[PDB]
Image (cartoon, grey):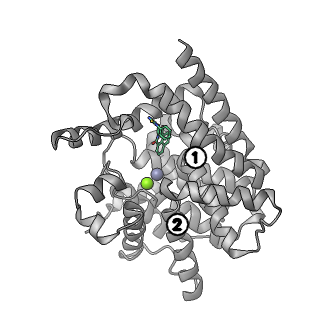
Amino acid sequence: HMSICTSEEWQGLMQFTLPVRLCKEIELFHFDIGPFENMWPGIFVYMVHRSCGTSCFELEKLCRFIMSVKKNYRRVPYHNWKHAVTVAHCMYAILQNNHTLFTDLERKGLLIACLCHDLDHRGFSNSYLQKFDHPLAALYSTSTMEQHHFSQTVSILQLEGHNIFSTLSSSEYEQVLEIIRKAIIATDLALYFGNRKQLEEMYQTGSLNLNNQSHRDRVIGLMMTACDLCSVTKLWPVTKLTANDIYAEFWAEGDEMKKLGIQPIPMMDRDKKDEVPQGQLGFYNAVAIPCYTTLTQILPPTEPLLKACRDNLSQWEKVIRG
Ligand SMILES: O=C1c2cccc3cccc(c23)C(=O)N1CCc1n[nH]c(=S)n1-c1ccccc1
Ligand SMILES: [Mg+2]
Ligand SMILES: [Zn+2]
């Protein structure tokens, strides 16, 4: 039950070359992929080749994976193909600015994870699936969709000529799958709040340590959160357009709850558009600012994400003042 990409799709990606005026600007954290839709698969190829190397994966296998991943994202307002690449980009930028801090296997795994991290998203949250006993909620009682997103990733790997990790040893093959499983489960915001508070307490008391494996998972978790909300780190007008995509997805989920007769949460209620500014202002103070605050403390090169998130909070404060 997986959509296989066509032969022309992946062939055309192999022959794609990134224009030189973009080479410079893909390295910048604030980079917006939005205006280059046709170039997204090739932008993921480029980022892989720059981070891990031109001989990292077999180009033929890699272009099948990417284009099959694209075909298994749905046409929903926010959690879609665009989002996957935007998240992969933010990781690339982070990884590029802290390169030798991570392994080849970790660099390999996290970009692959970011591209697959919302595979086959239906536009619905964990709470919606659990409340109306959806089959996927019966299968995965906690972090529902995220487990499915890992399970979808593993299925693409298992397709014919798609397994980019084939050439790793069976030991490294199961290492990088645990990196991918862990990184994709971390994208559930329900986990972020636990993760961040720990890292701050670890940081402030001086006990945070990167050769400590338990801590690598927590730092990778925060990076995966940092990337998943990177729409709040782009230039003001871009961040405002991505916000509309998000609410459109929340409001469709609202409509489904109103059909069954249940008042949704304000964030998912299209009649409470007035409060949205107070909703963003809250999200930045309670989630986003604290996220990049702790990320920049661990990885000082990731500061531009904190700066852009603050600059957008200012804009959200000006919105409320009229
Ligand atoms: O839920 C998300 C959200 C989830 C996942 C990725 C996101 C990326 C960017 C912005 C948002 C999100 C975002 O803005 N909101 C919440 C915004 C919001 N609108 N109304 C209320 S209330 N809130 C809110 C949610 C959490 C904390 C504070 C406010
Ligand atoms: Mg998700
Ligand atoms: Zn996501």
Q: From the top left corner, tell me how far across and down residue 126 is, in percent.
A: 36, 56
Q: Is residue 94 left or right of residue 252?
A: right
Q: Position of residue 276 (x, y in %)?
A: 44, 28
Q: Label 1 is placed on what type of residue?
A: Leu
Q: Residue 310: horizontal and vertical position, in percent?
A: 67, 32
Outermost residue on the bottom side: it is 170
For mark 2, does the 10 Å Cα neighbourhood hold few (<14), some (14 to 19), or many (20 or more) residues?
some
Of the pair 16 and 123, the residue shown nearer to us? 123
Q: Taking the image as drawn, is residue 167 in sight?
A: no
Q: Please state which amino acid type lies under the numbered disc 2.
A: Leu
**Disc sitting over residue 91 in the figure:** none
Residue at the far left in the pictured view: 260
Determine which residue is flagged by label 2. Answer: 59
Q: Earlier in the sequence, mark 2 or mark 1?
A: 1
Total marks in image: 2
Residue 270 seen in the current view: yes
User: From what the image shows, is residue 173 above or below residue 162?
Assistant: below
Distance, label 2 to label 1, CA atoms, is: 15 Å
